[PDB]
Image (cartoon, rainbow, N blue to C red; front, side, top):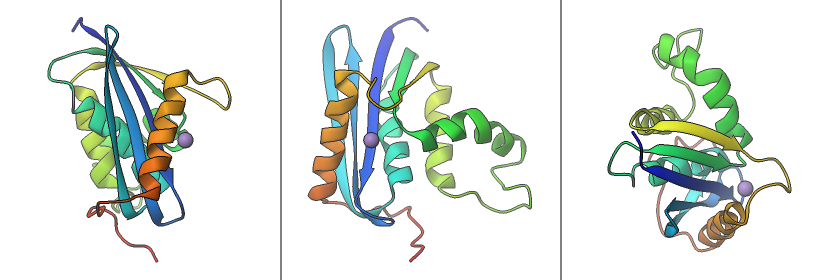
Length: 155
Ligand SMILES: [Mn+2]
């Protein structure tokens, strides 16, 4: 509905897989809600999905949200894969579970509850908020306190 909100999100990881973190800022009429956490072993992709997911789920009513992120991964999937998955039953052409299906589905459910406008940022053109989120993410990744139970260990 109405009620405007601005969300900034970033994800960080030290390896692949390695300790990682996310950072997100929920802003409404000047007020800011900050989010972040570190995980002992995760991926950059998953943190980037986790940042968007946490912020959105923090919303308790239909909102017009402008989602700002530097993630190429999140971008490709919102504009290139999400549609095919939905029509293919969250399965890859050759019928087979997509990577991070747990987070993509949960993020898609998150997006459904609001009218979203994506603001993709490239290189040095992101706002000051996109960098606070990066500091939060990198800080969390250096002091992880949680396990990413949904990550299928690939190594
Ligand atoms: Mn980043």
